[PDB]
Amino acid sequence: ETVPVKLKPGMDGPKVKQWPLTEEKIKALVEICTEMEKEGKISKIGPENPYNTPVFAIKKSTKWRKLVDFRELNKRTQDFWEVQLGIPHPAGLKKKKSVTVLDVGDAYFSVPLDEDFRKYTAFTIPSINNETPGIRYQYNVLPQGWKGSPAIFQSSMTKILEPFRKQNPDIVIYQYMDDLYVGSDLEIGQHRTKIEELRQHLLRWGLTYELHPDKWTVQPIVLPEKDSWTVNDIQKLVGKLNWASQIYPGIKVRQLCKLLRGTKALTEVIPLTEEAELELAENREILKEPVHGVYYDPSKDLIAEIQKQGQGQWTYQIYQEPFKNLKTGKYARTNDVKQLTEAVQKITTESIVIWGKTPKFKLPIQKETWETWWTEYWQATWIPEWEFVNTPPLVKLWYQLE
Amino acid sequence: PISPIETVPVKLKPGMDGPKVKQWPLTEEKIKALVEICTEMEKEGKISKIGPENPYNTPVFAIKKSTKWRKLVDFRELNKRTQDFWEVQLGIPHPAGLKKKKSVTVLDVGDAYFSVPLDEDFRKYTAFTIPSINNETPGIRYQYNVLPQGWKGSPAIFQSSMTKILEPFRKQNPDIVIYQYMDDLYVGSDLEIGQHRTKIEELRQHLLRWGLTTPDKKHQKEPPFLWMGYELHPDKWTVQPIVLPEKDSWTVNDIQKLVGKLNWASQIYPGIKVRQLCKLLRGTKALTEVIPLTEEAELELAENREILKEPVHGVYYDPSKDLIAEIQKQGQGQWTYQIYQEPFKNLKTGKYARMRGAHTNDVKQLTEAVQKITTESIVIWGKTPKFKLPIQKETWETWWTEYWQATWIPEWEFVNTPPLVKLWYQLEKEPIVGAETFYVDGAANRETKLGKAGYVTNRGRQKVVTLTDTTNQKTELQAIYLALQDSGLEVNIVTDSQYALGIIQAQPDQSESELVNQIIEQLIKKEKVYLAWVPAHKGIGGNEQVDKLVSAGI
Ligand SMILES: O=C(O)c1nc(Cc2c(-c3ccccc3)[nH]c3ccccc23)nc(O)c1O
Ligand SMILES: Cc1ccnc2c1NC(=O)c1cccnc1N2C1CC1
Ligand SMILES: [Cl-]
Ligand SMILES: [Cl-]
Ligand SMILES: [Mn+2]
Ligand SMILES: [Mn+2]
């Protein structure tokens, strides 16, 4: 039997155009979808269905894997998966010593999809050079990548996990989209034994990557530790600290600024006054801790900004209002787009664990270039929302590492 | 015939009924024409007579071609009420992506729409009425049994029907290539002339089995085929013949048309240029205004007319070989490229001439051109080409590893095709010893449009100018421009304008603003420039002083 699903009030289906794909990915999708159709998972559709959602192929191993971009359908289904059948996010997950991510997407293909909703899940396998019309399908079962799937499947999931949870009361298990996050405080060996155990449970129902959240540390804003200081050095310092003060209560620059008296040469060395030195220590002390006064608001979007730092290094912040940083961090290791792709997946994984939401990304790269290459390196089974920006050179500077 | 293919189910929009538009009274000759047309359509089964109970109507009209009448149905109301359909207009093939064939045959389907059945349950909504003379008596009522002309769903339903019909034939003849466009079919093969003809005959017979008539060998068009502004043979392609007018006087209309023709030809004629012609259209208003060609435009046109003098064709794609893409700089902002598999037999050519923003350099532009060509290549051939670029590995790598934006380009290599792209200057990474430090700033009034720019220096110097017709931002650039003119070959400059910093820091080599261009000249002249920033009104050393200066009277 199927659960009835509705779109949000007066919203229509998605009508998103399919992206052009390389030859090898088209071949892969063709074979994947032929097999899925033979197995009843999807059916061919006619021109009387005007909806479309883009589809991609990713390399998961050397076995291709279909990835459907349901970002728009998700947005238009939000009342359903969030308020009607929401899945609560445990605050305990982020405190665990180890968290393993499991793909349980295969689960969905054994639950039929509400017949009247099927049309909205239409997609198209394109041809090269538009030489033939694209092949059109829609889903007959819960699709991977749709936020409706876990929401609908969750009472089955609860029943599935019930024995395991009862037998290991200190293990935290959290479902987000196609994945299961499983956290414990066990030594690494014993943790892995429990994960294998969980998979056995899962396996009886056809459901068949290690994080360490309590080892996620704020990435402080760093103040230079100098032998001697030039006017330039002090000028940089004050700029940086001035920006910091828009975020962290208590940041002081008064004393440091005294040193900048008169119209002086950039390279002139200038000895620190003992109190400026103190001012510096205190600011340094404050920059270690999370920002006093910033709290997550569950009715608001998360935003994530990333800056390219050079030499395979990248900085990022997560906030809901600029400079109310909920989290700041870094990623390290050359192919700029591959690295950015990796950092985006990492930042998204942390946000899911921490808040149970994905951030909308501000990406320091031209739209077309990202669109061209992101799927070459993508491995995750979700896709965050994103947009493209030009990093203000000073923002880069102020978040610089050492 | 009417195809025995299953119909596509169709519905009106969720909260809507069928149309009910009243038939306008028609003149007698047009009533006659319609009775005669519908009588035939009726006998062929295209329409059926209906009763008075059917509550719906849509206006019909008739228009004299020639000495022939045509039946027109105004389906706006119905179209407004009909569901959306899967888009058919999703893109066309580029000839350069096609594979060469020994033979290609075109077959047009006769009375295409009228040869495809309409959803039984939807027919009622297409009811129309031939009005009686002066509307005295009830009109003759018909509804459609087939896809009507001018109805929303026809294009998409026709195409999906043709696709289903072709399906078994394609499965049986995997080495025959068929392209569908509107009511035409392009059928290509590598068979020898005799067996190709045989295969066409089988296609026709298969098509006829499914209700679709086509021209026989005697009536089939001969190559080259004209399609979408191209002209196609089995073994090469080009754009449709273009004749450039020879005229003394050129209206805006003429120049617009000429530019479109040139832009179109540029996909196979290498070197086509339109910049000088385009400048002529600047701020252009009346399509009838005559615009005197400038000497440069006159030469550009001539240089074009010469490129077009003799026919050029592109070759087709061979999937077993790599794509090679070469790019050359032509002028400023102007780029040109060619794509081939064997040198120098172009599959296609192109030009790129877009400014992303007001300020860029050649390294950024070349990278943008590479991206554009890369996207195009995926679309056309489903794979990336190997590039030959007029830039040194080191030049490109120094730039991108230093710049704050991310990028990646497909495999490439340097080719020595001047002009080469280089970096025209590089700002220092560290402040300069024994170089004068200039603190700069600027002010302007919001309702004055007046303002000042100036500098103070660590060696005691200063200056302030007055700017008319300027912004708070333009003054910021003026100040830096001041500092540059009055300084030695090495200078340190301290601004408090992120705006100005942003611009200069990106290391531009061209710009829309003449101010910026002037600054660019200065930067290229210097031996060393360090540029730094400080927050305004933090009581910083020399910044406070110059703020004071330029803010006087403002
Ligand atoms: O050059 C600029 O961008 C510039 N901008 C301003 C704008 C400005 C700042 C400011 C403070 C710290 C860092 C940056 C701006 N603080 C202000 C307070 C009131 C009004 C305007 C401003 N005031 C100036 O005097 C000035 O020179
Ligand atoms: C207009 C058009 C669009 C797409 N493909 C083709 C054509 N027409 C051709 O004439 C053609 C020429 C050469 C090779 N394929 C061609 N064909 C393919 C079908 C044999
Ligand atoms: Cl980790
Ligand atoms: Cl200007
Ligand atoms: Mn200023
Ligand atoms: Mn000022």
Image (spheres, coloured by chain):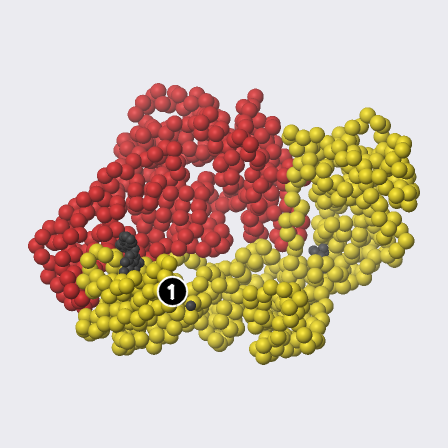
Chain colours: A red, B yellow
* Residue at the image position 74 percent from the left and 61 percent from the top: B226
* Percent coordinates x, y for residue B100 in the rendering: 69, 61
* Residue at the image position 84 percent from the left and 45 percent from the top: B62
Residue B287, by quadrant, is bottom right
Query: Is residue A69 visible to us here?
Result: yes
In the depicted structure, whether residue B329 falls above or below residue B73: below
Query: Is residue B300 visible to us here?
Result: no
* Percent coordinates x, y for residue B138 in the rendering: 88, 31
In the depicted structure, whether residue B301 falls above or below residue A259: below
* Percent coordinates x, y for residue A173 in the rendering: 37, 28
Q: Say which amino acid is labelled 1.
A: Thr
Image check: A177 left or right of A212?
right
Residue B136, by quadrant, is top right
In the depicted structure, whether residue B16 falls above or below residue B59: above
Residue B263, by quadrant, is bottom right
* Percent coordinates x, y for residue B74 in the rendering: 77, 42
Disc 1: which residue: B470
In this view of the protein, which residue sits in the foreground, B376 or B382? B376
In the depicted structure, whether residue B65 falls above or below residue B117: below
* Residue at the image position 17 percent from the left and 49 percent from the top: A252
Return the chain for callout 1: B
